Image (cartoon, rainbow over all chains, first blue to last red):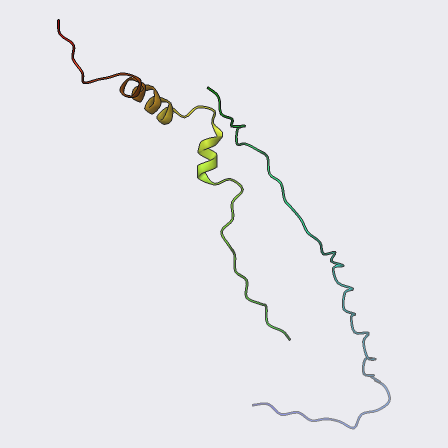
Length: 52
Length: 51
C-alpha cells in the first residue's frame, strides 16, 4: 500500500551492471593411489606354546 | 547433482572382549578350575580304604 512518483532522470547519476564474475573452478580432486594394505595392531595377545 | 551412495558400516573393533580377556597372562577362573580339578583327575576322591 504505497505510491511513488518518478521524475524524468538526468545524467547526474549513472549506474552499470556488474561484469560477469569469474566462476570458481572445481578442485583438482584428491589424487588417490590404490593398492593392497594390511593394517597391523599391537600384539597384546601372549605367545602361547605347549609345555609339559 | 548425484546422490551420496549407501554405505554399510560392518562391525569393527581393534580388540574383541575375548582377546582382551585373554591378554592377561593368568586367568583366575581357569587357573582355579585346573587346580581344583587336579585332585579329581589325578586322584580318586571316592574310593575309601579301610584296614
